[PDB]
Image (cartoon, coloured by chain):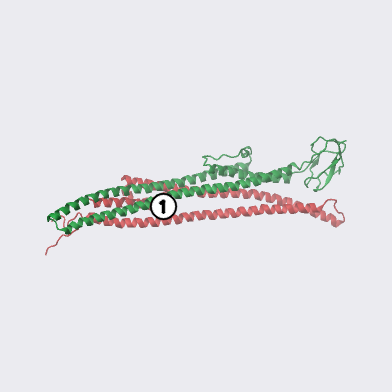
Chain colours: A red, B green
Amino acid sequence: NRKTVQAPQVQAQAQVDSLRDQYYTTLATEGRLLAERDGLSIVTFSPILDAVKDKPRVAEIIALQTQLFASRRQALQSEIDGYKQSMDGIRFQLKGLQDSRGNKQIQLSSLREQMNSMKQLAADGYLPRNRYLEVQRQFAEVNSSIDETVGRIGQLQKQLLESQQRIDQRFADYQREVRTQLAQTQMDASEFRNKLQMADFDLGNTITSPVDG
Amino acid sequence: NRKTVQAPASGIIKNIAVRDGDKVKAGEVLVQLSQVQAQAQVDSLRDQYYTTLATEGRLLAERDGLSIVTFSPILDAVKDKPRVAEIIALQTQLFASRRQALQSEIDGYKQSMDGIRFQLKGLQDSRGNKQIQLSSLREQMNSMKQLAADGYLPRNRYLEVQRQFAEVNSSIDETVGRIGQLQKQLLESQQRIDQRFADYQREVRTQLAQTQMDASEFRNKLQMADFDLGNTAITSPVDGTVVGLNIFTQGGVVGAGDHLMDVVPS
C-alpha cells in the first residue's frame, strides 16, 4: 500500500574533501610513528595513502613524513654515537690512569724494599748513616699519590656507568615520547574516520529510493 | 762567605760530573739523578694535559659553532705521539657526531613546523570556502524571507535555511578552534627549539668551564713537575773549585737535608 520518500555532490563533497586530507595527514603521521615505535629502517605508508600518491597534497605529506623520519633517526643515531665515543674517551683516560698506578706500585715496592734492608741492617747491629724516616716519608707520599690516582679512577668508572644510564634514559625517553604521540595520532585517526563516515553518509544523499522506477 | 751545596730532592744519583781539585763555571752540572720517576710524573701529567687540550679544542668550536674543530698548536707539535693522535681522532669523531645530532634535530623541528604549516594551509582554504557558503546561504535566507512575506512559502521551511546557516558557521568555528590550537603548536615547538638550543649552549659553556679548570690544574701541576725534573740535576752556586766529596756515593740513595759537597771561590 505505497511508500513515501522523505529525505532531509554539491557541497558536502567539499566537507568530505576537507576531512579527507586531515585524515591522510594523520595516516602519514601514524606510519612515521609506527616505524619509530618499532625499529624499522624505512617508513611504510598506509594503502589508503598508497592508493592516492598522485594527489599533490598527499605526495607532499608523505615526503614530509619521510624527511622528518630520516631527520629524527639520524639525530638519535648521532646522539647515541656521541655517547659512545664520550665513553671511549673515558675508557681512554682510564687506561693512562692505570699505567700510572702500576708504575707507582713499582716505586712503592722499591721504597718498601729499601726500608726493609735498612731494618735488616739495623737488626744485624749496623745502623745506616742514612735517614730511614726520609724513606718513610717517600713511601707515605707514593702511597697517597696512589690513592689520588685510584680516586680519579673510581670517579671515571662512575662516569661511564652514569653515561650508560644516560643512554638508557634517552632511548626510554624517546620510546615514551613516540608512544604518546602515537596514541594521540591514533585517536585523531579515529575521530577523522568516524566524522568521514558521516560526511560520506551526507553525500550519499543527493537521493532516491528506487533509482529508476 | 763560603756556601755549601745540599741535596734538593731525595732519590738515586745516577752519576757525578765532578771531583776534588776541579774549578766551577757558574751553573755547571755537578750531579745527575735517574729521573725515571720524575720523568714518569711529567709524562703522565703531559698526557692528561693533552687530553684536556683535545677536549677544549672541541668545546671551543662547539661554543662558537665552528664548522671544523681546530686543535692547539701544542697538540700539533706532539701529534706523532700515539695517544695524542688517538685522542685527537676521538675528539674529532665526538665533534662530528654532536654537530650532526644537533643539525638533525633542528631539521626535525623545522620539518615538523612545516607540517603544521601545511595543515594550516588546508584549514584556511576550508574556512574560506565555508565563508562563501555562509554568504550564499544568507542571501538565500533573505530571498526566502521575501517569499514568506508575500505569502508563498510558509515560515516553516524558511527557518530551515537558518538551521543550515548555523551548522555551517559552527563547522567554521570547529575549524578555527583547530587553527588556533595549531598556531599554538607552532609557538610551542618553536620555543622547544629555542630552549634546547639554549640548553646546548649552557651545557657547552659549563663543560668548557670545567675543562678550563682542569687545564689550569694540569698546567700548574706540570709546571711543578718540570721544576722537580729540572731539579734532578744539581748545579754549583759560586764560581771556583770543589771540596768535600763522599768519594763513592755514585749510585746510592740520598735524603733531603743532606749536604754531600761544598764549592770554593778564592
Residue A32 percent across, percent down from the top left: 40, 51
Give the side of residue B213 with respect to residue B262, left or right: left
Can see residue A168?
yes
Tag 1 residue: A35
Residue in the picture at 63% in, 47% down: B214
Residue B59 percent across, percent down from the top left: 56, 44
Dot 1: element? helix
Image quadrant in which you'd find residue A144: bottom right
Residue at the far front in the pictured view? B149
Residue A47 percent across, percent down from the top left: 33, 51
Tell me which amino acid carries mark 1. Answer: Ala
Q: Nearer the viewer, residue B56 or B83?
A: B56
Instruction: Count residues near mark 1 (Cα–Cα under 10 Å), then give few for <14, some for 14-19, many for 20+.
Output: some
Residue in the picture at 63% in, 43% down: B50
Residue at the far bottom in the pictured view? A1
Q: Nearer the viewer, residue B26 or B18?
A: B26
Q: Give the position of the C terminus of chain B as an image quadrant.
A: top right
Give the side of residue A15 with respect to residue A211, left or right: right
